[PDB]
Amino acid sequence: MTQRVTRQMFERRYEQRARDEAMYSIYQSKIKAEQKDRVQQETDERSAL
Amino acid sequence: VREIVHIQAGQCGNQIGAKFWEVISDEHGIDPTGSYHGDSDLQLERINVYYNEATGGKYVPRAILVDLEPGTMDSVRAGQFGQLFRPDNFVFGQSGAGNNWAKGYYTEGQELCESILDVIRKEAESCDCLQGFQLVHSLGGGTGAGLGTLLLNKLREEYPDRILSTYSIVPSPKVSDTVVEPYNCTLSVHQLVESADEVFCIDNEALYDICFRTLKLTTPTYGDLNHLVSMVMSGTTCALRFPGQLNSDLRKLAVNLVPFPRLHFFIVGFAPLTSRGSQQYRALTVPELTSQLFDNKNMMAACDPRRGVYLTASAHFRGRMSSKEVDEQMLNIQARNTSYFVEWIPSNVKSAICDIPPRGLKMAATFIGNTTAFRELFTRVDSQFQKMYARRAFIHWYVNEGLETVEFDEARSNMTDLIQEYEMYET
Amino acid sequence: MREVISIHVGQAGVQIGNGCWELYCLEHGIQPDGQLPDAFNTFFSETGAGKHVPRAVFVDLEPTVVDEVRTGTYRQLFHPEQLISGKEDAANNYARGHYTVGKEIIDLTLDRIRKLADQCTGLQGFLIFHSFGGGTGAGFGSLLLERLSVDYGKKSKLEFTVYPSPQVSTAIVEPYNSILATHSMIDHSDCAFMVDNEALYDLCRRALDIERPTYTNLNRLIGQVVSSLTASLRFDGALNVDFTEFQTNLVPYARIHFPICSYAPVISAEKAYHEQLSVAEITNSLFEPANMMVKCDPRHGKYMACTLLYRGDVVPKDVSAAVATIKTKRTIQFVDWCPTGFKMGINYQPPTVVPGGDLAKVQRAVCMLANTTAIAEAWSRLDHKFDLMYAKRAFVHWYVGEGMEEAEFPEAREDLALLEKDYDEVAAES
Amino acid sequence: MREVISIHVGQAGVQIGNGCWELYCLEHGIQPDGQLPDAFNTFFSETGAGKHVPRAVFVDLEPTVVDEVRTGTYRQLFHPEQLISGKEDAANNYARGHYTVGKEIIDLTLDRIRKLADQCTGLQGFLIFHSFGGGTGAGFGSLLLERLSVDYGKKSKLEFTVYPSPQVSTAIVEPYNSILATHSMIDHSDCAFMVDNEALYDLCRRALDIERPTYTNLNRLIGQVVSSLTASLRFDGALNVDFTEFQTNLVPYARIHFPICSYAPVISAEKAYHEQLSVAEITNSLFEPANMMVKCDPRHGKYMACTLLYRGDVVPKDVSAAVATIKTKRTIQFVDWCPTGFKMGINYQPPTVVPGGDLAKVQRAVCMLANTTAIAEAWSRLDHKFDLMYAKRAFVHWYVGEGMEEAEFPEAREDLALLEKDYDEVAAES
Ligand SMILES: Nc1nc2c(ncn2[C@@H]2O[C@H](COP(=O)(O)OP(=O)(O)OP(=O)(O)O)[C@@H](O)[C@H]2O)c(=O)[nH]1
Ligand SMILES: Nc1nc2c(ncn2[C@@H]2O[C@H](COP(=O)(O)OP(=O)(O)OP(=O)(O)O)[C@@H](O)[C@H]2O)c(=O)[nH]1
Ligand SMILES: Nc1nc2c(ncn2[C@@H]2O[C@H](COP(=O)(O)OP(=O)(O)O)[C@@H](O)[C@H]2O)c(=O)[nH]1
Ligand SMILES: [Mg+2]
Ligand SMILES: [Mg+2]
């Protein structure tokens, strides 16, 4: 029992970039956005200063 | 024990059937080559429900695959789990149906019906006790709708006692893949109203929305779309497959939910649904499941129940939980939203518990209910049907197959009666 | 398992057919000699040992075009019985190719097409190519359809023809051939697609990056459209569409079969490096008035039919979002009679590129087939052109002397007039 | 922290921007060299050393106007990349500025605009300037907005454009480019403000006492309006309004998004000493049609609602004592379905004067932005003018030759009629 699930392996391998790899970029960017959000608090504190 | 025969029709049915038997194999722990490599003796209690046993320690599922063209069958013949499927169970034609409902019913459905009925009878009389039939089909017109309703009638003639529970994917009423949907859907409902006992409606558009909002999938594949539907089917039959603190079979569901013979269409849903990342932070409890079950965004039917009112509601659970928690949650959700339930039916919420949860999730649930919100779907397809019938476009194909236009008026009259009945019972 | 058979009439059909079968052999991995260096049964047959044969027959009344295939590299593939060549062509005369000379070879051709269908069990469909301007293409196609209509009955007969261009022309008697052909296809043809060389030249120049295309490049573009249409029968997909599916969906009546074609992306092999061309990108490009291969105004043409065949890595949700976005456009007005108005076919097999070709290596592509009322614009142009010449009896003597009765001209004229009346009636609201 | 990007297209946009950035340099106290002799970050970037730099992009398809800034006094303030100049202008032709010449430079500017957004942490939206009659303002302006709609999506794209005057006209083809531009802005633009030169000429003569103004004087009055618009973002104030607060209150109705503008008190430096200029006085001056920046009478139609902005000494209760009297005026036609209609904004930074200016050192001032059905009067005049050209096809050949398809001419005409239907449908009552 190969041909459809092999196509499914091919089909999910192409979706793999719309899968997992979409998530690695967004959660890494969210982590960097937290480092950005905290310098926002630092810089708004500088503007408060 | 208490057996069920599974029938799959056409492109949509076979694809769902493949996913369904994947999940069922995972539940019971069946290696795709046929050997049992499970982990619990509890899987062996009611493995007879869905499977026959072949000599040499191999199990053959009670699955019959039906089509008019070999394209879907050649897709499933190597499938992924198809080595379980018996080679003689594969029945197929040599002609693309064309999705002409008259063609699929009279021209080619009749020729194949004799062969499918005998193949059905092979597994029907090979079980200690048949209890009901399971059918998966789409309301397209060629084989899922036309041939499916024909076999449903023939099985009703053969087995008046048994339960004909069919799963239906209605054409999506904003975007769907053929212009002849209003004709085929109108005729299919007409046959399904009288002959079927339980009809489950699932919409592709709501399936897309659930994947985005809850599953956070960038692009919903047909694979995961069929996976959610397979989970719903397995949860429905999980009570028969494993013990529980309060059991509920198909007949118990049918008697409880259906007040009147015609009004028996059902909306289904599943919980818990969680994204791949945030499942670690969730505190999954019974109130969490209840909130997800009654949430209007977890309903895989694109008909907001808040517009209408509820008539009956059912809840299934899988896992070890306290029965008082389930009872209190059902009472709270019933009393908190009295504006959405009929006054003349007290205790509108049914409950059920299963001992073993699905693999991967410590606790799970399934929601099936009946509401008057179905009036929107029928009205939408009726308005589409009215336009096409007024212009009498596309009807020459159906006339050439021998279907006379007076049959369309009967089908519309039946839907108008169903729409009126739903309207008056809301009061 | 499931089988298709093709017939090619005229040099336009043969040269288009030449390009198509090189496309299939590269797609299926078959050397020109016919041995491998699957879907094969749809188009090819295994002759034992290690050689294949195509399910095609090439017919023309002149030997030059057929002899070119006999002398070419692809001569080893084809069967000598499949190559049928006449002696003298119709000389751009419908009457000459219909009665005097077409009847000489019609019986021989019908034998070979029926004989090859005996080996072809799971059969549903025919593919026929025509050149409307040429006398042989229109005349022989009329007689061939008349015979095939009664010999086979309810069988899917689909044609891929070249419509005369609104201004570009190569024959002065072209309007006479087109109207007489239109009179016979309108009853004997289940559904036939047409393209015009004028828009093919225009698209090959603007979106594609060819300064001066020849017929070879245009044939390659046509072959890609054919390959996309037949992709469903050869490869698995999320939504496969059969020949019978197209016939039911595309037409709302009997005589309004004529669809129009659109293919995207059509970007060249050089400029395509810069664009990802997502689902939304290609979907929007299809409905551009410039991407049509028929020079018709979509503003005057309402839509009551559409078919969106995608090829490559495509997810159905993105199609659902793209189609929903398209429907919101006010400029693209569907008819009131067609709420849904869509067929979609998604297939996991990417398109194919040919060495020495002109198309880009696109990961995903979509071919479009729709029916619009704008085709009635072209019918008026042909009708007026026919009326101008027939008013003074420009070329009556040639057709009359070749066995055609004079009274057939008003009969076809009335047949075309009824077709235009039908288009106006159907397009009107109610 | 919170920032705005201003981009200018056409000669009108550039010289309007020249006046606006002159005002900002004086208001914040930044020398023309970029050094100092706060809210700076909203309009400027602190590059180190002692220098700042505006967040602006100047675009025109011809170097004359841009090189004036390059050779002008302010040249050291701007970044050389921000100044983008083409080779040859669009010649007041929409087709030339959109398809042929506009696409030669479109991707160069978008990189420049997007690069500025990278340094811009708290970006809110855009300010865009046009001249409807200009070829670059309309042809290139349409192409820029269509790209920016898909480049950024949910960002507030506000526009401030120069409309053709009711009778004063400098270009014959002005109605053609105006309507073709209207279709593009009406969908992609978030909101677009309205001003015209003819009303400016009358106001600059009556209220300000100038016999014979130039484009220089008109630009500075435009400069004050945009400063009061942005005052709530930059300086302190009890009530602030921004681009999630201006857009919703002012123009909610999907296609009714065209407001009108006004400013008060507008008075010469000689006479301003003799009045007291209470909040009641300046507020009453706004509602007179004579002060309208657009030569349309609100009495002809109905006020939908307004949006008033005060600066400087203004006291809160004084506003609500002045504006409560507005309802008592019968002539100010508020429909019953808009019952509140008076968004408020108060800022403590007074207006700023310019050397060689035309305004007085008024301690307090007010700006007005309202939508009214009276703007449908302006659209009717443009519509009637266009039909007179298009019935006899007065200028079609110029547009078609430059890549424009003729089918767009009725389509843009159709959209304007639908827009006119929208305004009349809004004027309906229940
Ligand atoms: N696109 C394209 N069109 C072609 C090609 N070859 C011929 N044509 C079309 O064919 C028409 C000329 O008629 P023929 O191709 O000779 O048709 P025929 O069946 O041979 O008819 P006769 O030659 O008159 O006997 C022209 O209008 C062309 O548009 C080709 O290679 N590519
Ligand atoms: N109020 C005002 N209007 C201006 C000014 N400069 C140009 N305009 C308007 O601009 C219109 C002419 O178009 P252009 O100034 O050339 O704008 P454009 O988009 O660059 O047009 P092209 O030069 O053809 O590219 C005139 O009708 C004016 O109304 C100005 O300084 N003040
Ligand atoms: N959810 C889901 N729907 C599918 C899938 N494949 C096909 N469909 C739907 O099934 C319908 C086609 O049904 P079909 O098998 O042709 O029925 P028939 O024409 O009566 O034989 C289409 O409208 C599809 O939207 C799938 O993998 N998942
Ligand atoms: Mg020839
Ligand atoms: Mg200019």
Image (cartoon, coloured by chain):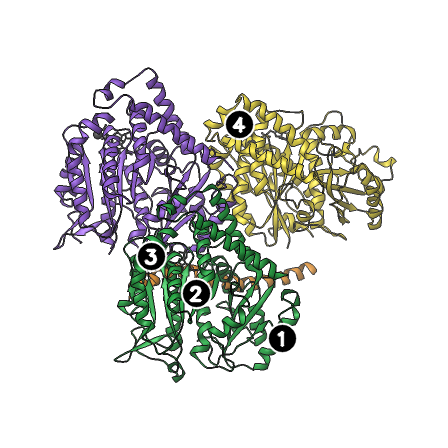
Chain colours: A orange, B green, C purple, D yellow
**Distance (Cα) linking label 1 and label 2:** 30 Å
Mark 2, chain letter? B
Label 4 or label 3, whichever lies nearer to me, is: 3
The answer to whether marks 2 and 3 sit on the same chain is: yes
Residue C313's x, y, as percent? 37, 54
Residue B38's x, y, as percent? 36, 80
Residue beneath disc 2: B166
Q: Tell me if residue D71 comes above or below residue D247 in the rendering.
A: above
Residue beneath disc 3: B109
Label 4 sits on what residue type? Ala
Residue beneath disc 1: B331
Circles 2 and 3: CB atoms closer than 8 Å:
no
- Mark 4 residue crowding within 10 angstroms, few (<14) / some (14–19) / many (20+): few
**Distance (Cα) linking label 4 and label 3:** 69 Å
**Distance (Cα) linking label 2 and label 4:** 69 Å
Cβ of mark 4 under 8 A from ligand 2: yes
Label 3 sits on what residue type? Gly
Label 2 or label 3, whichever lies nearer to me, is: 3
Label 2 sits on what residue type? Thr
Label 3 or label 1, whichever lies nearer to me, is: 3
Residue D314's x, y, as percent? 81, 47
**Element under disc 1:** helix
Residue beneath disc 4: D91
Label 2 or label 4, whichever lies nearer to me, is: 2
Cβ of mark 1 under 8 A from ligand 3: no
